[PDB]
Image (spheres, coloured by chain):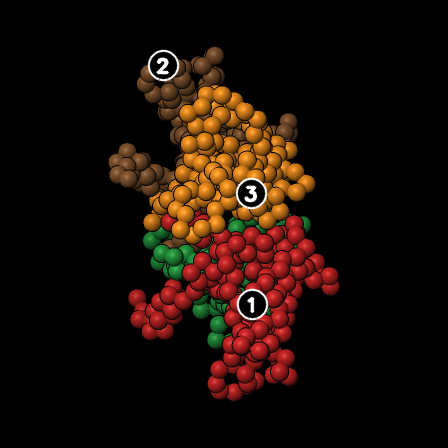
Chain colours: A red, B brown, C orange, D green
Amino acid sequence: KWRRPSLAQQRARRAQLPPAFDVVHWNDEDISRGHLLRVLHRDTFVVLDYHRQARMLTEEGNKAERVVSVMLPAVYTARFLAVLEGRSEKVEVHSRYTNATFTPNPAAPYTFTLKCTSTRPDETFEWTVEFDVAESLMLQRFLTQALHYNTGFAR
Amino acid sequence: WRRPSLAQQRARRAQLPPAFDVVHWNDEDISRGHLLRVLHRDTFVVLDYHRQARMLTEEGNKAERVVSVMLPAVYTARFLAVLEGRSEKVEVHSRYTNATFTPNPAAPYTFTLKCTSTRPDETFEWTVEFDVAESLMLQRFLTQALHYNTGFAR
Amino acid sequence: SLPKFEIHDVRDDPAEGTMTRVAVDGKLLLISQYPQLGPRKVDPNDLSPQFDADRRISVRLRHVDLAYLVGVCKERVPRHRMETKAYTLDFEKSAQGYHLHGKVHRVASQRMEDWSVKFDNHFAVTLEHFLESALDESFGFRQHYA
Amino acid sequence: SLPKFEIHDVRDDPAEGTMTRVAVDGKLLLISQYPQLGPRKVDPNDLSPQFDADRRISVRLRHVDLAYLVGVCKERVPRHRMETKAYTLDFEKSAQGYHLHGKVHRVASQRMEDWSVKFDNHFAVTLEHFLESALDESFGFRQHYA
């Protein structure tokens, strides 16, 4: 009948924060090429938070720093799912801040690629996130849950 | 809108055991009509087999329960194995039931539940065919039963 | 408010515009469609409705029909035909998505008419996910355990 | 208590018996196994444990490993190898079910040993359902929306 301090604390954290999963691509060998994409669900939007690796994993401080955040309206969920499920060969997202595509990666079955060119007041930042077999499956289940909940099936 | 009957209806669906019905009425020949209710109650999957009591045209209860088979949680994966094609058969053996659940070779993705029920010693033999839709409902139902029984909704 | 998705297809020639709704109430799928009412709206101040409820189509399916529709999505069966006094409909998977068609009648208008609606591309994915979700939530586990 | 399933494999020869547990804590799968302790228990009065928690194996996987295991179930990959400071384990799909095997150490011991556990027949179905459920619930939607 223990008393768990942290266990109680992280329980509430997980519950309050947005449902999400992380696509981690660290690279201490070369910090400039390491990145983190956190995929979350907040206020009916699927949010893609792209981060660059800050410092090597072998040191204090936050290992990542958020560089750009793309918010995808609910209508894009089914279009991304269509690519993950093999019905569509591509989905394009166009905004005055984002121009991105999500497509299958020829290199291996069941793998996909997110390529994006972001812009802000005139600044521009190009980034790519590869999804291997596991990461793609994670995105397909995540989007499946987001569509299920956003549709109202858990009310 | 104030919807009292509708509110009472949802209170009933929430309170009663999660379930679905396999309905095989036969007004043409009442003796061939039947209803199998598949439910989840207290960790068990329960099979309530009913005979048709009256034509759907007359008044009163259309079904009368004849036998109820309570299946321990362990049978869930065994029935799922048959539905999913990994197993060719599951046999349920107890003091009061001797039953088999197998794929029906006459149509893909359909299955047959055949049972001989005994009681302290009267006996009663019954069979319920699950067509493609009923089979799929059974598979989704057992999938949900296993999910909730395992603790995933706590 | 029931779980649902809607396809808004507003046209220039209103004669061909429709709003199609697919909703579920427990075990029962409600598929409805509203013909466009008038030209495409433009003025944000215009609070009139874009579609016509008085001329809507509204069909209700049984729990087993929801399971047959999922079976067509999973390709366990090529198609499913449903017949009631109110309608005669076939649901089949096409190369581009799904096709629901047959004879129905609009509200308060006893008079049958040919009708067809397709759910293609991303709309096919939307329909697939909605039907699978609906079937899984149709037994009452979530509410019972809550 | 975490969602989990257990396989109690009690044998006449204690040496071969085990209790295997698969649990999940949010994103993290916890796989444990306890060696049988002594002969099969026959006296309901005996309060000694049938298995030995003090000689258990206990491994923790990463969120991405859970996704890889589902991918093996779905046949998108034939094998997933996991290497950490604590263990080296392969998970693969066999004709009868699934096989998880490699090098691990028991509790309070740095002495590595060869270990193998299989989930065959209805236990392969139990494992597949558990992994798909765990991956779906791993994002936090249910707890967030509640």
Q: Which percent across, then down, holds residue C36?
A: 50, 38
Q: Quadrant of residue C143?
A: top left
* Residue pictured at 60% horizontal, 76% vertical: A124
Seen from the viewer's position, the closer of residues D88 and C80 is C80
Residue type at mark 2: give it: Glu
Residue type at mark 1: give it: Arg
Seen from the viewer's position, the closer of residues D32 and B102 is B102
Q: Which mark is residue C72?
A: none
Circle 3: is it few (<14), some (14-19), or many (20+) Cα within 10 Å? some
Q: Which percent across, then down, holds residue B26?
A: 47, 17
Q: Which mark is residue A96?
A: 1
* Residue position for label 3: C11
Q: Which mark is residue B58?
A: 2
Q: Quadrant of residue B3?
A: top left
Q: Secondary structure at mark 1?
A: loop
Q: Secondary structure at mark 2?
A: loop
Q: Which percent across, then down, holds residue B109?
A: 60, 34
Residue type at mark 3: give it: Arg
